[PDB]
Amino acid sequence: KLVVATDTAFVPFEFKQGDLYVGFDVDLWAAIAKELKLDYELKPMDFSGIIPALQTKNVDLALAGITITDERKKAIDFSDGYYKSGLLVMVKANNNDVKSVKDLDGKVVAVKSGTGSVDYAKANIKTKDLRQFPNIDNAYMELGTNRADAVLHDTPNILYFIKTAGNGQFKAVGDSLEAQQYGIAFPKGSDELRDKVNGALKTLRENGTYNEIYKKWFGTEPK
């Protein structure tokens, strides 16, 4: 009866393949849930509503490739950390001007509301304009129709999109910024539960299951 909030669409961590939801988080959690004997149903939602949802305790926990920041640590709890990510710039295939993250002068950057991509862009870039959208597909399309210069979002995400959907239309520029970890988020006070999911996480690590989930989605082992 645990309800776990996930992202509407965050390839390749959770997305709709036909009927059900599919992805790295979905599997990892199905594995943890299996390990612990938890019963649950998932509940996808636009990322923006997830932290609020945990806070209002409308959902019991959440996976949506959610970055651990100590800023967020004030509001919710996090497990002991499951995937090392970062941020990457995406522009159009034959874009010329941008080599960088220097949109830092007067470029229009599209991002997804509620995410650390907005945090980072605010704190680090002098954008002429910054467009926020409920989901990243809206932001890709802003780039594709020439209404933004770049998109900035999670490395794995703009990497999975380029090689699959976005192929020949878009490219990554530079290397991964903002080395960060995803973790499973909980309401505050859910420590019978969290100091425990951590336990399962270390088990999936030790028994090699993590390696095969990862391998499934990224094409190699972690190490």
Image: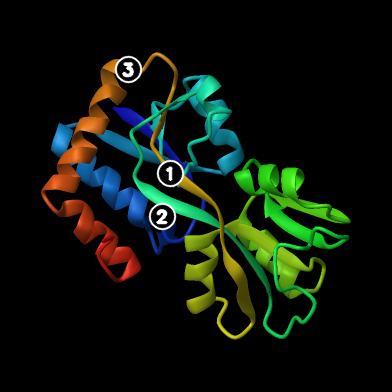
* Residue sitting at x 54%, y 20%: 74
Residue at the spot of label 1: 182
Instruction: Report the coloring of the rendering.
Output: rainbow
Task: Residue type at mark 3: give it.
Answer: Asp
Give x and y (percent) for residue 217. Answer: 32, 64
Q: Which mark is residue 191?
A: 3
Q: Which mark is residue 13?
A: 2
Label 3 to label 2: alpha-carbon separation: 25 Å
In the rendered image of this protein, does residue 10 appear above or below residue 67?
Answer: below
* Residue sitting at x 46%, y 53%: 85
| Viewer-closest of 139 and 45 | 139
| Viewer-closest of 190 and 145 | 190
| Viewer-closest of 77 and 13 | 77
Mark 3 Cα shell of 10 Å, populated few (<14), some (14-19), many (≥20): some
Give x and y (percent) for residue 67. Answer: 49, 41
Task: Residue type at mark 2: give it.
Answer: Phe
Mark 1 Cα shell of 10 Å, populated few (<14), some (14-19), many (≥20): many
* Residue sitting at x 62%, y 62%: 137
In the rendered image of this protein, does residue 190 appear above or below residue 113?
Answer: above
Label 2 to label 1: alpha-carbon separation: 11 Å
Q: Which mark is residue 143?
A: none
Quadrant containing the C terminus is: bottom left
In the rendered image of this protein, does residue 107 appear above or below residue 115?
Answer: below
Q: Are marks 2 and 1 in contact (CB under 8 Å)?
A: yes
Q: Earlier in the sequence, mark 2 or mark 1?
A: 2
- Farthest top residue in view: 189
Quarter of the view holding residue 184: top left
